[PDB]
Amino acid sequence: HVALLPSAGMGHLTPFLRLASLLLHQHCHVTLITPQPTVSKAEEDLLSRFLSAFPQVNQLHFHLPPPFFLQFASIRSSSHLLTPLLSSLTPPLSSFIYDMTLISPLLPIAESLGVPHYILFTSSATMFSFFSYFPTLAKSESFPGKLDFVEIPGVSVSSIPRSSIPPPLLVPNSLFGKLFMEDSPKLKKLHGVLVNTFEGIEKLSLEALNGGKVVKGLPPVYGVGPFVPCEFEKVETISEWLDEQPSGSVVYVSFGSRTAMGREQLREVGDGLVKSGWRFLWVVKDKDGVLGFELVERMVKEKKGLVVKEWVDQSEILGHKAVGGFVSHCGWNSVVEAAWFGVKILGWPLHGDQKINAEVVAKGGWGVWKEGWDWEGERLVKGEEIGEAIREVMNDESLVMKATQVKKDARKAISVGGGCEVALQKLMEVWK
Ligand SMILES: O=c1ccn([C@@H]2O[C@H](COP(=O)(O)OP(=O)(O)O[C@H]3O[C@H](CO)[C@H](O)[C@H](O)[C@H]3O)[C@@H](O)[C@H]2O)c(=O)[nH]1
Image (cartoon, rainbow, N blue to C red; front, side, top):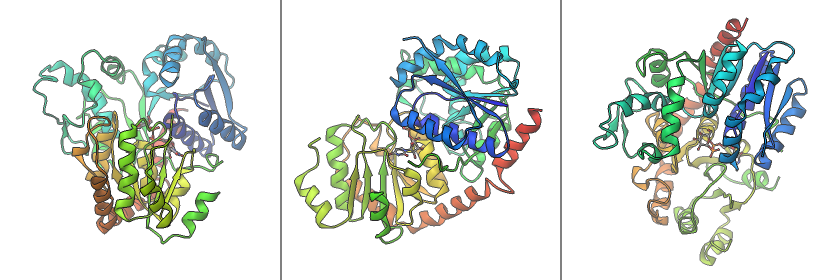
């Protein structure tokens, strides 16, 4: 009997439910905690579509008193409502896995239940190393004054520069600065950490965390990745356009679930897509007259472009043989999915941990990103730079060779060898 509690956003719910599908395939009784009302429609649509495919799971409504960052505040202030709900739960609980963003409000609740509690870090293991090493950084407070690099002993990245550090972590009066210094020291009071990653992309980061060379006192981390896409996530004009395209010729473009860019940069993106000369599938989120008539015509005249304003199935598009590239913000959910389908990534990091995640795939030899593009809103990337980066990555056949090997290691990390199978079964015996 396992208890799950994800945070808000599709970036947190998609990996959590993929973990539940793995636990259910290992024959578990999963009790999913659902903080209602849920934020986005795509979340509650993914829920009932997941609940329908698995009627055996026990959904537990977490009712909060009276958006993504707003539900953040109501849960951590009302986390004491869960320990009466989880104590009178039959069958008796055997474990509890929640999101890392909720490690502080749920640790007292988890310790009071007396069950082995864990966290599911939805980002990379390398970012988890930066998250764990951050309290050590702030105490040697030549920071952020003289700090030029962040050298974590033995991680998969060579050296994390100052440019790749999340900007709010360099400001002393920010939320994430306080959140990092408050959440990270509580990792030691845990039984373990699940991370959606496998040995084929973060071998050195996984071994450095378990080897005790990142920070002293960490619990064992478990690479239960890759979280392969499931069928309950699928809710058909897009697939019919990709079918009539040469394989490995479509450029998939997506920046996650929010895409909070500006109207200035969006014009250059679409302009850069047509200046590259490759057929593309652009996915944009508004939350409209931005596209140029000279570009809208060329998108239709050249028979190359697709632009959509809808929650597409990224797994099908990455799984389609026509898609050979991926312009990604390098959200770890998109990265692991891109690794599973062997689609080389063009890195365009925007906020937070996306510069570090982009270097993880860059060191792996199956991804290329430009340090000079910087964070979102810092400057304007011209369409020529975007057209050149796409031309550079698409012409680069060395990436698909490494991307293929990353696909092989991904398919090998779920089955007989399977660091996921090893980690999951190692957790089952502990939960006895
Ligand atoms: O049109 C779309 C857009 C997204 N997705 C899916 O929704 C998820 C999006 O997750 P990403 O990590 O790609 O994007 P987010 O912006 O949600 O990611 C954020 O939250 C993640 C979870 O914490 C990571 O931390 C990440 O670094 C951070 O940017 C993936 O399953 C992706 O395939 C779709 O199916 N269709």
